[PDB]
Image 1 (cartoon, protein in one colour):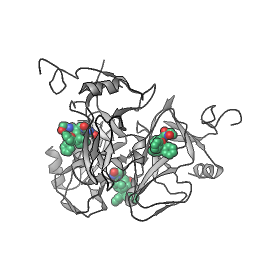
Image 2 (cartoon, helix red, strand yellow):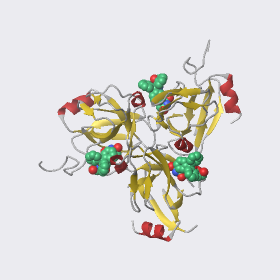
Image 3 (cartoon, each protein chain N blue to C red):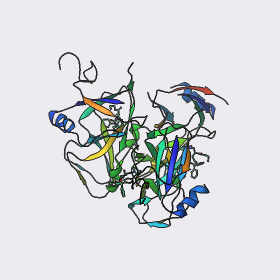
Image 4 (tube, protein in one colour):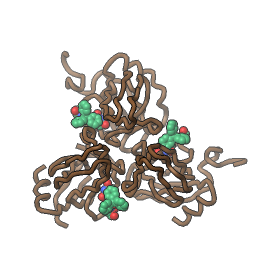
Length: 145
Length: 123
Length: 136
Ligand SMILES: O=C(NCCO)[C@H](CCOC(c1ccccc1)(c1ccccc1)c1ccccc1)Cn1ccc(=O)[nH]c1=O
Ligand SMILES: O=C(NCCO)[C@H](CCOC(c1ccccc1)(c1ccccc1)c1ccccc1)Cn1ccc(=O)[nH]c1=O
Ligand SMILES: O=C(NCCO)[C@H](CCOC(c1ccccc1)(c1ccccc1)c1ccccc1)Cn1ccc(=O)[nH]c1=O
């Protein structure tokens, strides 16, 4: 599956240009937290990941999945919607709905990795950074803006 | 991915006559979920899938705004299952939570992630 | 999808010899603390063959009646992986919770959703992590 990713700021583009953390094989592509943020106790926060994305599998545009990373387990953070379903047609900012199950506020930091994108096939993924997803303003393409 | 769905009462029939990767399922009767609880919510339907195949029950994205969570994370509905479809919902709140006929909390989805089609059926 | 499973002790081998989703056993009695996440070791390593493929660890439906929930929602096991399989279990109760040898809380499933088979095998490949090769 091939992901095309629009970074919504230069600071995000800088994090994905220097990705680190993804290799040959890998069924999941880790996404970054892009800004320090405090999640309230006993709350759901809708955390914006600073990117938009489409997946391609003669080419079709496909739905894909947003999984928690394994290592989220050691934190009190849980993915509210279990596994996120990103539809083929979605062009908005990718967002993680994180339940803070603790009674203390929880600090997430720029460069933390809590979730990863995954293909319905389970096959290795690759990605490239792109200026737009399609011609629409929401896809960040087309005349003007 | 094609579903043949059997509705269980006529008023559920009506709901599904009156409707991309997932097919939203309706809450079929008003119900109060106790605080800190897990409730098995019957969805008024049985269903098979043709592509005879297994399929998945995901929470809908919008469940996140509520304090309800699917207890078994993602439901796995085996090719062999003929029973009514049931969502196990935890209410993570200290308060009761009311769910209404027509609420959409849960969706069916195929292992391929390809857009889904259904027909109502009676057997 | 075909799974090749190494049991990490003879006791575990006995359980899998006498056995869509393939259910995995709890292999030792253990007490989960209240309000906790525990990495429960399942005493097996496993590979899925189609060549090697990624696969998924779901909770079983019946986990819903307990207070135990899978902390990472659905586990993703990469094609590589040769480590012991672990279930990350949240005990959402304020009492300790007893799991027992033979309980079934979790299951392996394919990304295809195809029915699966397994055989018990002595090594996954030649490496030590695969339980293979010289010295084993
Ligand atoms: O299609 C969408 N949005 C359209 C723009 O609104 C989805 C997310 C649905 O948006 C949520 C939301 C919508 C309605 C009620 C409650 C929440 C959302 C839900 C769950 C996870 C992530 C996002 C949303 C939209 C905008 C701001 C905050 C939340 C995209 N999506 C789906 C799963 C997901 O995990 N992340 C994500 O971005
Ligand atoms: O085979 C099933 N049901 C009836 C046959 O026994 C499955 C789910 C298992 O049934 C539960 C249950 C079984 C054993 C202990 C506790 C609960 C169940 C669990 C989780 C989700 C939904 C249903 C069940 C069966 C009958 C009444 C209430 C719950 C089908 N299934 C699986 C996932 C799911 O999300 N919904 C569902 O209906
Ligand atoms: O690839 C792994 N381990 C390599 C050794 O690190 C996995 C899970 C990541 O390992 C955990 C862990 C790592 C880092 C921080 C916290 C936990 C883990 C997390 C979630 C579920 C199961 C295991 C781990 C590794 C070693 C001992 C205990 C936990 C394998 N995996 C993935 C999903 C899963 O559900 N079960 C599992 O065994």
